[PDB]
Image: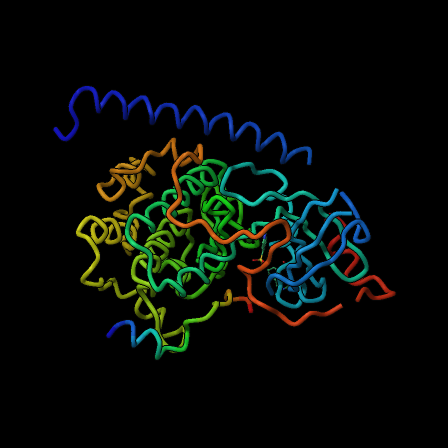
Length: 346
Length: 20
Ligand SMILES: O=S(=O)(O)c1cccc2cnccc12
Ligand SMILES: O=S(=O)(O)c1cccc2cnccc12
């Protein structure tokens, strides 16, 4: 067969150790989920890092920098995101993984909800990808491996993520990925039905109004790996409806510089037939982790953050924001409480 | 090229989620 005796025994033991790690991780998650912080004047507001509202760099007045997310309650209501948003705070307080951004404080006032997270200073993968143009296959693989491990973790907790895209992946000071934005994350032991996500990254079963499951995240991983290695996504067009036509068609074309191993992996991730899509089969995530394109990946070394990253962003000190774009800076909290009943639990 | 078609699409910037 493909593996000799030593190799097969090593892989077997590695897979059983993953099961052991995940069982403990699910126990910690459920304990925190069952039994889950500050105020606006505790922080000096510095500048706006990104755009329901804005994310701002703040300095806690222990001197540490954080990214403070500000959500207008009326906006959350108008976009019908009330349950998605209360759930995002609950998920972020309860999970724990090296590639998931860490929530440190939460609170609210008359008009806004606030989530204070660790500041990830290296900027969005999106910016780096558009600037460099495309990532080499080893560079794309280093990032992909972190997403594989992160989805393996989240899916073991029965959480579907549903918003993978380079815009939602931050690069930290060591060049590793931080997943942000859990507004669409949900516990789904079986199926769920909400039409949500980003057009380029939607699995066909979402577009076709089906009940769907965590397999949509593995489709989205295929889209991400393709966009990282090509510089552009596998399905695009002027308007979303034409993008959906390409996604459901069952056809994908690849750049001539893609390796044969990469094309084979992507044809198995970007698989319209759910009975054939990697991540959705009897062997689960092992079909992905054991694929030839990942043969050089040391999964435990990635998890321990012992692999040298291909890209280390510029860090000129604490509070440096040079990796983020510039946005217009605004100041206001209403004298009356907005949407009090809808957000009582936040 | 496919890259030129990507530029022509107008969807090269940060992309919004559906609910926007
Ligand atoms: O904003 S929520 O309350 O979360 C919400 C979720 C789903 C459908 C909705 C339809 N009309 C109003 C609100 C809705
Ligand atoms: O500014 S954003 O890119 O929207 C963003 C969102 C959530 C957490 C973040 C942590 N550090 C930097 C930026 C962050």
